Amino acid sequence: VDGNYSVASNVMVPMRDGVRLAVDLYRPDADGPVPVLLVRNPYDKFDVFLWSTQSTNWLEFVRDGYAVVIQDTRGLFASEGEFVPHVDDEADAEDTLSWILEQAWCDGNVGMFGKAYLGVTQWQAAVSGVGGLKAIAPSMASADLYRAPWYGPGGALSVEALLGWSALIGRQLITSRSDARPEDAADFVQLAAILNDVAGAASVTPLAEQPLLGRLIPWVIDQVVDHPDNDESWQSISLFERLGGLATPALITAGWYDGFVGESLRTFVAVKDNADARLVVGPWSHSNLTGRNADRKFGIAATYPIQEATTMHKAFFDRHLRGETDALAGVPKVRLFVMGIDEWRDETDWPLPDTAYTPFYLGGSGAANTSTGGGTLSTSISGTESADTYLYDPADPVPSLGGTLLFHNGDNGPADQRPIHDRDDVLCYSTEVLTDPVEVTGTVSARLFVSSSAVDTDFTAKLVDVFPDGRAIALCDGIVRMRYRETLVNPTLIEAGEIYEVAIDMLATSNVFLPGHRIMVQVSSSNFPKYDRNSNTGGVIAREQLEEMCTAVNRIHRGPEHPSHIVLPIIKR
Image (tube, rainbow, N blue to C red; front, side):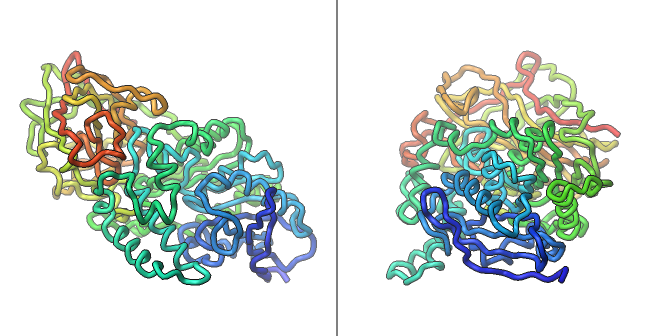
């Protein structure tokens, strides 16, 4: 009977080391083997409602004749073994694919889908070399775990991401326990207190002392906090350098305010030349896919389009797992939600073909401190040599507000920035009010001439759309930790007072700045707890006490010989 299926629970799958991983089998009521879709899930294979609304109506796949396998990853819930994030998923996925391909009901075609960690596990599957894996669909995910979500291209720790995710893993473990432990009730309450105040949890110094999280999941310290350089421990789990050698079609989703967005987009660039890659980017954050935010509404068309996504995934799997050569007819290569005009729009490529990477130079009379300063942005080089100066005090960092926050207030990506506009350490530069629209769609970076009183510090850059009513809406932002200014791998300190030209990777966006709006950039030296705060000492930041940290006098240089600017991907149509 087409449309009908059965579900077998806790089928145990043996890995190479003898440890057995538990799976659930959703198999169509049909004769002969079928194509198979695999989901590798650390959040309980039984709990399908937890994530499915953020992905696909995948029971449609089963009703249409796909088998679907959902697996507890190693050491979690019904699976045997010990859980350590990332380190076992390459080998475990390879063995799981091998097992599936051996099964009577598998016709030799396997795909995958899923979001975030369930997207990462697909890149880890794809590097295995198993020919039966015909396509993946990693949503809002990453193939380089240092660059997202634990650190980033600027070499700062994503501390709210780390502590928030670790606290949810901890609550998961406690809830899933066989026999409740005497300390379970108190631990569970303490993990909730972290999640109710992530910035406060991130404020304890030394950062590396995590009595609760370090006990429940030692990897928090042993791997992430203790390895601030993009060293061999990170490279061991990175998939990115191997993506270029793959020929695996990938249906890649991203969100402009999602923590993974930079790495999601880079996976598309890395695989598009060697197989059929597809890109969908909506205006979502990791936990807010509704299109509605406190001070910014994108319209109901911006809500994560689960039905259209289900249709697109099925067409994708029909093409690559069923060999239906016309199944993707009419489907665009790239589909972006273009903010400002707040409309979905199809494109032929990412980056967009006719992107004009355009410098907008920092300028202005007087000091650019606060939003009532004199800071300007212009496509012409500034005529007079100037500099803006501020005190960065680690005890008083610029609070994170929107952006790509994950767990600390991670449901308000396009946040109004006015609550921090009067801070003296927030330098503001903006264009005149626009009379014609300016579209900025692509990757975004800044190039700043900076100096510091300290031997290490951070610099941040944030792109903002200023609305006529005064809302200053965050778009994309980035950070550079100065010791990593040239390499994330082999950091060196800087000389106090010397001027450096540094790049700040500000991820990506798609926004039409409409007439009556302004383009604005904020520059500072902190963005906390989105990123941990630089101690301004050159020390091992995560091991320092707040008392041991220093303030830094930091300076942006701007003018003819120091043409600090933001590089905007200008689209003109």
